[PDB]
Length: 256
Ligand SMILES: [Co+3]
Image (spheres, rainbow, N blue to C red):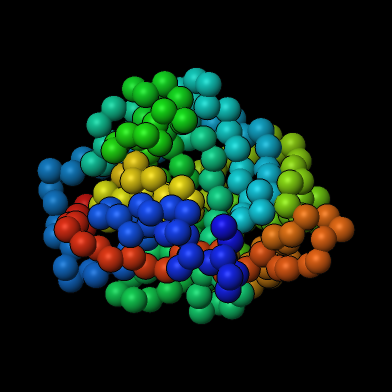
């Protein structure tokens, strides 16, 4: 699978039938339709003991991986029961500033979207978690182009070393708190992974407040490669799936 013309999102269903599932992601968030929910508890994002250890170009995107063998960086509260461990984060972005995000808001597309993936500790490991309906909690944060995001630069400045499919590089001591906006107001709905195998194991938590990154910052993302070394060059751009049928779901809001 890929994002190209012969192996893009509208092809995934052939190898992966759950693509036309009942709780697929991403979706469009219609703000006048999301109901404020007061029984939602405030989000709790406990990242001060986070341990980052590697970044990898996997042929689709780049993942920054964390030590999840302990309860270091964890998400709880909001619509969540129990405790969720951070395992990695990545981005989806476009070939132009006017597209790139996966979620949209009142049909508006942002230049990119950050995904912080967590797995429920009651299932012991990520492999087992993805087989469960509340197996994962993903934090989704929109990127708009404006002034730079200081917290992002150290990520940007390693991409050269991981330019092609399969390359990796040590990434320790990175603090994911520097990628968070001021507000934790959010929307939440039940959904899925947005790449194959598209498993319907995710509680989505999408922040209302975007972060701002610079045009230079986004253009370094656009220099990465989908291909392998010594392979024909194809830029890593437009690695986003478009919005899927909301179907029988309700999006809830934390804020009035
Ligand atoms: Co993602």
